[PDB]
Structure formats: C-alpha cells, structure tokens
Length: 76
Picture 1 (cartoon, rainbow, N blue to C red):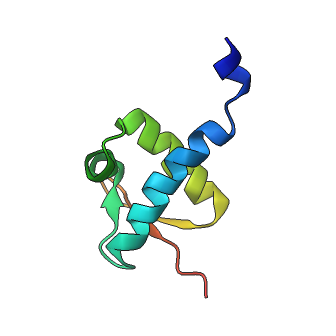
Picture 2 (picture 1 turned 90 degrees about the horizontal axis):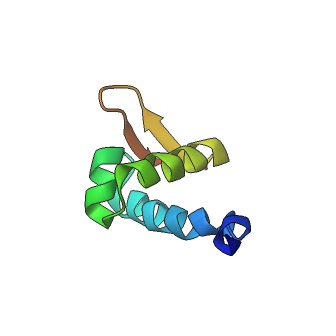
C-alpha cells in the first residue's frame, strides 16, 4: 500500500527507458508502442502510459497511423 503514494517518480524511470530508446532511433523511423515494449521489455500497457506522458510532456512526437509510431520531437 505504500508503493501507491510513491508513484509519480515510478513512471519517470519508465520514461527514461523509452526516452533514451526513442533518442537512439533517430528523427524519422518512429517506433510504435508495440516496438517500445520489445526494444525495452516493458509491457505495452506500461509503454502507452509512459508514451503518453512523454507526448504530453512535449518531448515525444507521435506519428498518426496504425499503430501510431513515436519519435523524439526535435524541438530546436
């Protein structure tokens, strides 16, 4: 029950896992959350959660499609 209030930073560790990977990919060939769980290992349910947290942060760049791909948002 204590791990519940200790959340917040809990997904931050997950964000780094996806963020670092999205950075190793390269602005162009975005990866889909399905691939995120593979390149890293985290289950899609955790990938989408973190993927949205990044997209909502202003650092990720989702690509419309099916499934949609995710790539670091080059904000020069």
